[PDB]
Amino acid sequence: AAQTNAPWGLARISSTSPGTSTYYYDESAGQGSCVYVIDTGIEASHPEFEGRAQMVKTYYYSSRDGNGHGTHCAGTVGSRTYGVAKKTQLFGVKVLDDNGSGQYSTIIAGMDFVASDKNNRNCPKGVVASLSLGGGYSSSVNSAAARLQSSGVMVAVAAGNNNADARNYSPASEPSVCTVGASDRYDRRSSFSNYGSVLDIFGPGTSILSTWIGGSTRSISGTSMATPHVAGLAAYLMTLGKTTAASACRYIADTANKGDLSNIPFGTVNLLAYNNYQA
Ligand SMILES: [Ca+2]
């Protein structure tokens, strides 16, 4: 399949070179997979989600996304126009309030929730979790992310936006999950992107167009935006039968565009998520 004039990030993920604008992907498009977006929620009624999105959990007085961040992230995972996996099922878990904040205890609870909750969902091709959030190092937070992964969910987490080594952030620093740095449309490491040995992969994170609340759209930047590209990619590859929750991060790294990014600090991987789709 080919989607012309796609957001640059989508085109980038299906290209061996920067500077193109068409997104190429197998029509299966993540059908039969599920992606949990653990964030400020998801505006499920957005036309862009086509009935494929649902809120399944909140720790606040509403499950509505009163911020937009979670809806943007979900849009990158699987919206019809702005999504990597255009046929995946999206499940929203609201661990962040409408200011985008959340206590670590609530974040942990949301991760453990998804590990159980996947047994209540129909996801024959497999399960992914996208965590576009983080804070300072916490062994408890890292352990929760490790549990979620161990339970059979492909966990993708943001490296963080401090232009700093991600070893000092959680869940970014957890070895067993897929930690995602951010790049721009010229294949530069995004100026704010964290880096370090704990990173597994980069995806598009600068000036990313996606869904927003009020049934709108916007371009924003962050490792928050890179993460759902990787989460969507994993879902898409799982439906194709190329990989599984346990091996998807390795598989993406194995099949990544290699050595193409600039300003990657010595010791950080130079790998950019790529779907290896031959139209
Ligand atoms: Ca890892």
Image (tube, rainbow, N blue to C red):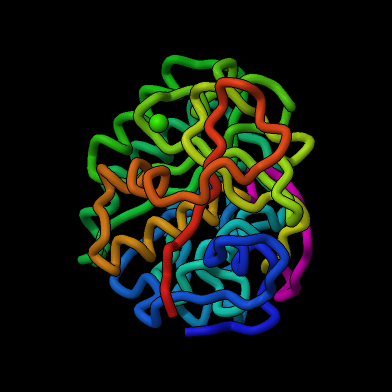
The image shows residue 189, relative to residue 32, as above or below, that is above
Quadrant holding the C terminus: bottom left
Q: Is residue 263 left or right of residue 167?
A: right
Residue sitting at x 56%, y 21%: 267
Q: Is residue 168 left or right of residue 209?
A: left
Q: Is residue 50 left or right of residue 127?
A: right
Total number of numbered labels?
Answer: 0
Coordinates of residue 172 in the picture (x, y in percent)? 52, 28
Q: In the picture, residue 141 is in which quadrant?
A: top left
Residue sitting at x 24%, y 44%: 152
Return the residue nearer the eye: 206 or 34: 206
The image shows residue 25, relative to residue 117, as above or below, that is below
Coordinates of residue 163 in the picture (x, y in percent)? 74, 27
Q: Is residue 90 magenta?
A: no
Coordinates of residue 119 in the picture (x, y in percent)? 21, 54
Q: In the picture, residue 147 is in which quadrant?
A: top left
Q: In the picture, residue 102 is in which quadrant?
A: top right
Question: Which image quadrant shows ligand 1?
Answer: top left
Coordinates of residue 131 in the picture (x, y in percent)? 51, 43
Residue sitting at x 29%, y 51%: 117
Return the residue nearer the eye: 76 or 139: 76
**Region in magenta:** 213-225
